[PDB]
Structure formats: structure tokens, C-alpha cells
Image (cartoon, rainbow, N blue to C red; front, side, top):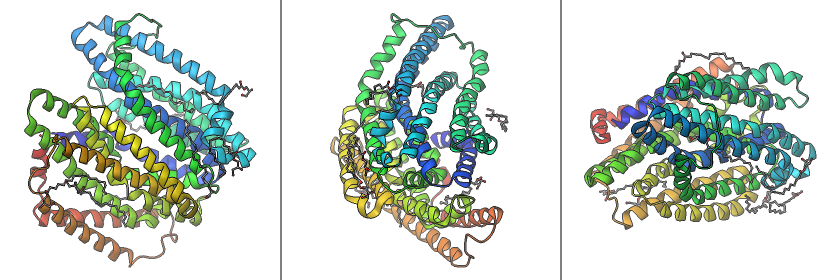
Length: 510
Ligand SMILES: CCCCCCCC/C=C/CCCCCCCC(=O)OC[C@H](O)CO
Ligand SMILES: CCCCCCCC/C=C/CCCCCCCC(=O)OC[C@H](O)CO
Ligand SMILES: CCCCCCCC/C=C/CCCCCCCC(=O)OC[C@H](O)CO
Ligand SMILES: CCCCCCCC/C=C/CCCCCCCC(=O)OC[C@H](O)CO
Ligand SMILES: CCCCCCCC/C=C/CCCCCCCC(=O)OC[C@H](O)CO
Ligand SMILES: CCCCCCCC/C=C/CCCCCCCC(=O)OC[C@H](O)CO
Ligand SMILES: CCCCCCCC/C=C\CCCCCCCC(=O)OC[C@H](O)CO
Ligand SMILES: CCCCCCCC/C=C\CCCCCCCC(=O)OC[C@H](O)CO
């Protein structure tokens, strides 16, 4: 049951996600949304996101299958040797990249955030934070490799808990080290650094428990390393396209007023809060199922899995996007507006979040529909569609920046994701790969009715409540949780009244 899989993934990631939002709230309270946070987000978050794009789009899809074949077809000694050579090559490459990026950090910041050049102190702070960021890439890459090995041995709780330590270390660095750092946010940077270390050392004993903890070594003649490189080859183009798109979006953001990057960051975090599970969970668990369907010839199961993923997208991401748009002020004020995060920052974050809610659905649908081509050994069509999406994204950025500013950049990304999803779906329909099952009309009608009930309940409750800035954090968060509970319970109650049953949707998972 893939619904069971999504529940398990949610339960395993809950604690880390909660602490990540506590960390974001601490950052907002102590540093607000200004030049220092902009420098931190450009220097740390952008390289981390580029690294994650490369790791999940290229490295893992090549390393995990070869590791599983070593585990199942070869012995533990040959597998340990393969792991040692993999880790050694990764460590050497990332050490070279760390050195080169520390030496070239000013030009890196220059081309990724040109608008920062009119403020020399902000630029220097960004370059300094990037110089601290670069070793974290190597640390967190080794930690990710450990997590992948542990997942291959069916150990998912430990890697899903690992980022808790990063969040805790960042929080402690802000609370205890920021008063002693000359630019205070510098402490946060080191809190990330130590975090990486912790995330590694937390997973090393478990690696030793399964007999897969080995010293790294270098070898340019290992069969497995060449197998992984050959499988990594055809994904570099797809990785580079999304990397370039993110870099140009950052370039556009760098020319806006101080705080725009931070407002966008807080908005996208708020958007990720309820739907962080579905996005990646559905994709990673649907790709192997559809691959097996296509290999066995069971086209009915392929169609049913795809249709179930799409219907779950409609059933869970749509109400979240609508409710996030409606509750933008309650969310921003109850979660962020404390200390140096002012009401102005709250309003700007609300604008960006409302812009992001338009494309939440496009993102969740893209992550489900891309395996429709990936499972059939088709990397070319998603890359073509992604190139077109990049072109449209930059066109809309150029058109929207002067008037809508940061919110306009967010809306550009949202519309681009929407049309990315639509192009993927229309390609699937065109090649006769997928055709939806019967009963989408009644499904959508009941969905619309439940959504109307939810919106009515939300607006009714919001019309009765005092200004959200009055009251301390306890009061605000209690009110927000109560309103969210009422909205969600009304939505699911309407869904049940109109015929939706949990058993019936679980049967479509498998
Ligand atoms: C809006 C300003 C005029 C148009 C700029 C388009 C730049 C396009 C290319 C950027 C990549 C990096 C190349 C180097 C860019 C340096 C830009 C710079 O330093 O701009 C400082 C200025 O004060 C800022 O308003
Ligand atoms: C820079 C300074 C860094 C200082 C770092 C200090 C870290 C202290 C540890 C706290 C434990 C974390 C919270 C534990 C809460 C319960 C954890 C638990 O039981 O988790 C089991 C796990 O899910 C099974 O996989
Ligand atoms: C104020 C609120 C702002 C935020 C709002 C967030 C939600 C927006 C999403 C709407 C769903 C639209 C779905 C349209 C796409 C599905 C139908 C479709 O694609 O139909 C053509 C297809 O070819 C048939 O096979
Ligand atoms: C916000 C828009 C962009 C982001 C989201 C992109 C969604 C892409 C399509 C998803 C599956 C749609 C399946 C539609 C199946 C319709 C089948 C049909 O013929 O339905 C007959 C019924 O009577 C009346 O619809
Ligand atoms: C790996 C690197 C890949 C690089 C790929 C090439 C990037 C070339 C430049 C992009 C557009 C820059 C546009 C800059 C000017 C538009 C923003 C103008 O922004 O004004 C801002 C102002 O604050 C309100 O209007
Ligand atoms: C059907 C859809 C129904 C609605 C779906 C959800 C919509 C968004 C609501 C989220 C509330 C989250 C409340 C808790 C947020 C985390 C707060 C926390 O633990 O830390 C923040 C604090 O400020 C640190 O000091
Ligand atoms: C234009 C200049 C931009 C400069 C700023 C960005 C530089 C760093 C980004 C990527 C390189 C490093 C990529 C490292 C990938 C490691 C993959 C890995 O370890 O993956 C383990 C596991 O498989 C995971 O699931
Ligand atoms: C991980 C990424 C590594 C970099 C990827 C390519 C970036 C190319 C961009 C611009 C030219 C940069 C030329 C840099 C020439 C050396 C500068 C140098 O060594 O400067 C030392 C000085 O002390 C100050 O740190």
C-alpha cells in the first residue's frame, strides 16, 4: 500500500520537519528579513539546493541500484570495497571543489547575486558565508551517502531523523553564539557546519551495525564506480537545466530591495509546511512501482497507479494551497512576526506565499508525472519540457519583476510549474501512454463542493477573530491550530458526506 508508505514517511520525518520550522522561526525572530538573512540564504541555501538537485537527480539514481546489486548478487567484502571507492572518489572531488569555490567565492557571489554589488558590506558578508558553506557540502554529501546505504539495508528511521541534529545545532548557534560573532548571522553559518558533522556522526554506528562502515580509498579501475558513472551520464543535462533556472532566478532576485530573498524563503517554507511529504514521497515510491508495471506488461496496474497518484494530488494539494492562501496572515503573524520580524516583513511574505500557492499544484503534479517517462526509460522528453519551462520562467521573470517584485518572481515560478505539469500530462496523453480512468467528473465535483465548504468555514471563523498581532506566541499558535483543525475537519467531513471513502482510495494504491 503506497498510502501506507506515505503515512510511514510522514511519521518518520515529522520530528525533523517540526524542528526545521522551529529553526526558521528562531532565524526570523533574531535576524528578521533583511541584508544579513539575504546574504545567508544566497550563500548557503542556493549551493545546498544545487547540490541536492545533482544528488537526487543524478548520483542517487545511479548509486542505489548498483549498491543493491552488490548487496544481493555479491558478497559483503566486494560491497565494502565498492563503498570505499565511491566515498573516496566523492571525497576527493568535493575537496577539490571546496578549495576551488573558497578561492573563487567572490566571483561566484558576483554572478549569482549581482545586485548585491551596490552594497559592499552585504557582498562581503555573502562571500564569507559562502566560504563557510563550502565544507558543509562535502560533510552533508558524505552524510547523504551514509543515509542511502542505510536505506538500501531497509533502515529508514535513522536517515529520516538525521536532519534534526542540523536544526538543533543551528538553533543553539543562534541562541548562544550569535551575540559573540561580529556579524551575528556568522554564528548561524557555523551552526550549519557543526550540523553537518553531527549528521554524519549520528549515522556512522548504524553503518557499522550492518558491516558497511569503511575507510575511503581511491581507485580508477573499480567496475562498480564505472557502472555508477555510466548511469550518471545521461542525467547531467536534466540536472544542469534546473540548476541554471535556479541560478537565474537568484540573479533576478538580487536586484530587488533588501529582504526580498528572505521573504521568498519564508513564504516557500510556509508552503512546504503541510505538503513536504507528498512531493518527494509519491515520486520515489511511484517510480519503482511503475517501472515494475511496465516491465511485467501489466498496463492496467500502470494506468491505475498513475491515476491514483493524480487523484491524491487533487485530493490533498488543492485544499492545502487554498487554505495557505486564505490563512497567509495568520500563518505569517503567528509563526514569524516576533523580535526583528516586523509586520512589513509579514505582509511581504504573505504576498510571496499567495504567489507560490498558485504553483504548489503544478509542482506536486510534476513530481508524479515525470516518473511516467522515467519508468519507461525516457529521460529526453522531461528534459525538453524542462528547457521550455526555463525559457517561460525567465520570460515571466523579466515581465513581472518591475511591478510585482519578489511576489512576481514567485508567481513566475508558479505559472512555470503549472505549465510544466500540463506539458508532461499532454505528452503522456499524446503518446497514448496514459489515459485517465472513468469517474473524474464526479471526483472533481465532490472535490469542488468540499473545497467550498472548507473555504466557507475558514472565512467564517476568520471574520470572528481579533487582530492576529495581539496576543503572545501561545495565543496566536493556539488560534491558528484551532482554525486549521476546523477547516481540515470540515473539508474531510464534506468529502465523506459526498461519498469519498478511505478504503476505496487505499485500494487504488495497490
Ligand atoms: C539592473 C541593472 C542593469 C542590468 C544588469 C544585467 C546583468 C545581467 C547579467 C548578470 C550576470 C552577472 C554579470 C555581471 C553583472 C554586474 C551587475 C552589477 O554589478 O550591477 C550593479 C548595479 O548597481 C545594479 O543596479
Ligand atoms: C553546536 C552544538 C550542537 C549540540 C548538539 C546537542 C544534541 C543533543 C541531543 C539531543 C537529542 C535530540 C532530541 C531527541 C528526541 C527524541 C529522539 C528519539 O527518540 O528519536 C528516535 C529515532 O526516531 C530513532 O530513529
Ligand atoms: C486565491 C487562491 C489562489 C491559489 C489557488 C491554488 C489552486 C489552483 C489550482 C487549480 C486547479 C486547476 C486544475 C487544472 C488542470 C486539470 C485539468 C486539465 O488539465 O484538463 C485538461 C486535460 O488535458 C484533461 O485531460
Ligand atoms: C493548475 C493547473 C496546472 C497544474 C496541474 C496540472 C494537472 C494536469 C492534469 C492532471 C490530470 C487530469 C485528469 C483529467 C481527466 C478527465 C477525464 C474525462 O474525460 O473526464 C470526463 C468527466 O466527465 C469530466 O472531466
Ligand atoms: C550559471 C550561470 C547562468 C547564467 C545565465 C545567464 C543570466 C543572464 C542574466 C539574467 C537576467 C538578469 C536581469 C537583471 C535585470 C532585471 C532586474 C531589474 O531587475 O530591475 C530590478 C529592480 O529592483 C526592479 O525592476
Ligand atoms: C485541508 C487543509 C487544511 C489545512 C492544512 C494546513 C495549512 C497550514 C497550517 C499550518 C499550521 C501549522 C502550525 C504549527 C507550525 C509550527 C510552529 C512551531 O512548532 O514552531 C513555530 C514557533 O513560532 C517556534 O517558536
Ligand atoms: C556557478 C557556481 C555555483 C557554485 C555553488 C554551488 C556549488 C556546489 C553544488 C554542487 C556541486 C557538488 C555536488 C555534490 C553531489 C554529491 C552527491 C551525493 O553525495 O549523493 C549522495 C546520495 O546519493 C544522495 O541521495
Ligand atoms: C565551486 C566553484 C568553483 C569556481 C567555478 C568557476 C567560476 C568562474 C567564475 C569567475 C572567474 C573566477 C576566477 C578566479 C581566479 C582566482 C582568484 C583567486 O585565487 O583569488 C584569490 C583571492 O585571495 C580572493 O579569494
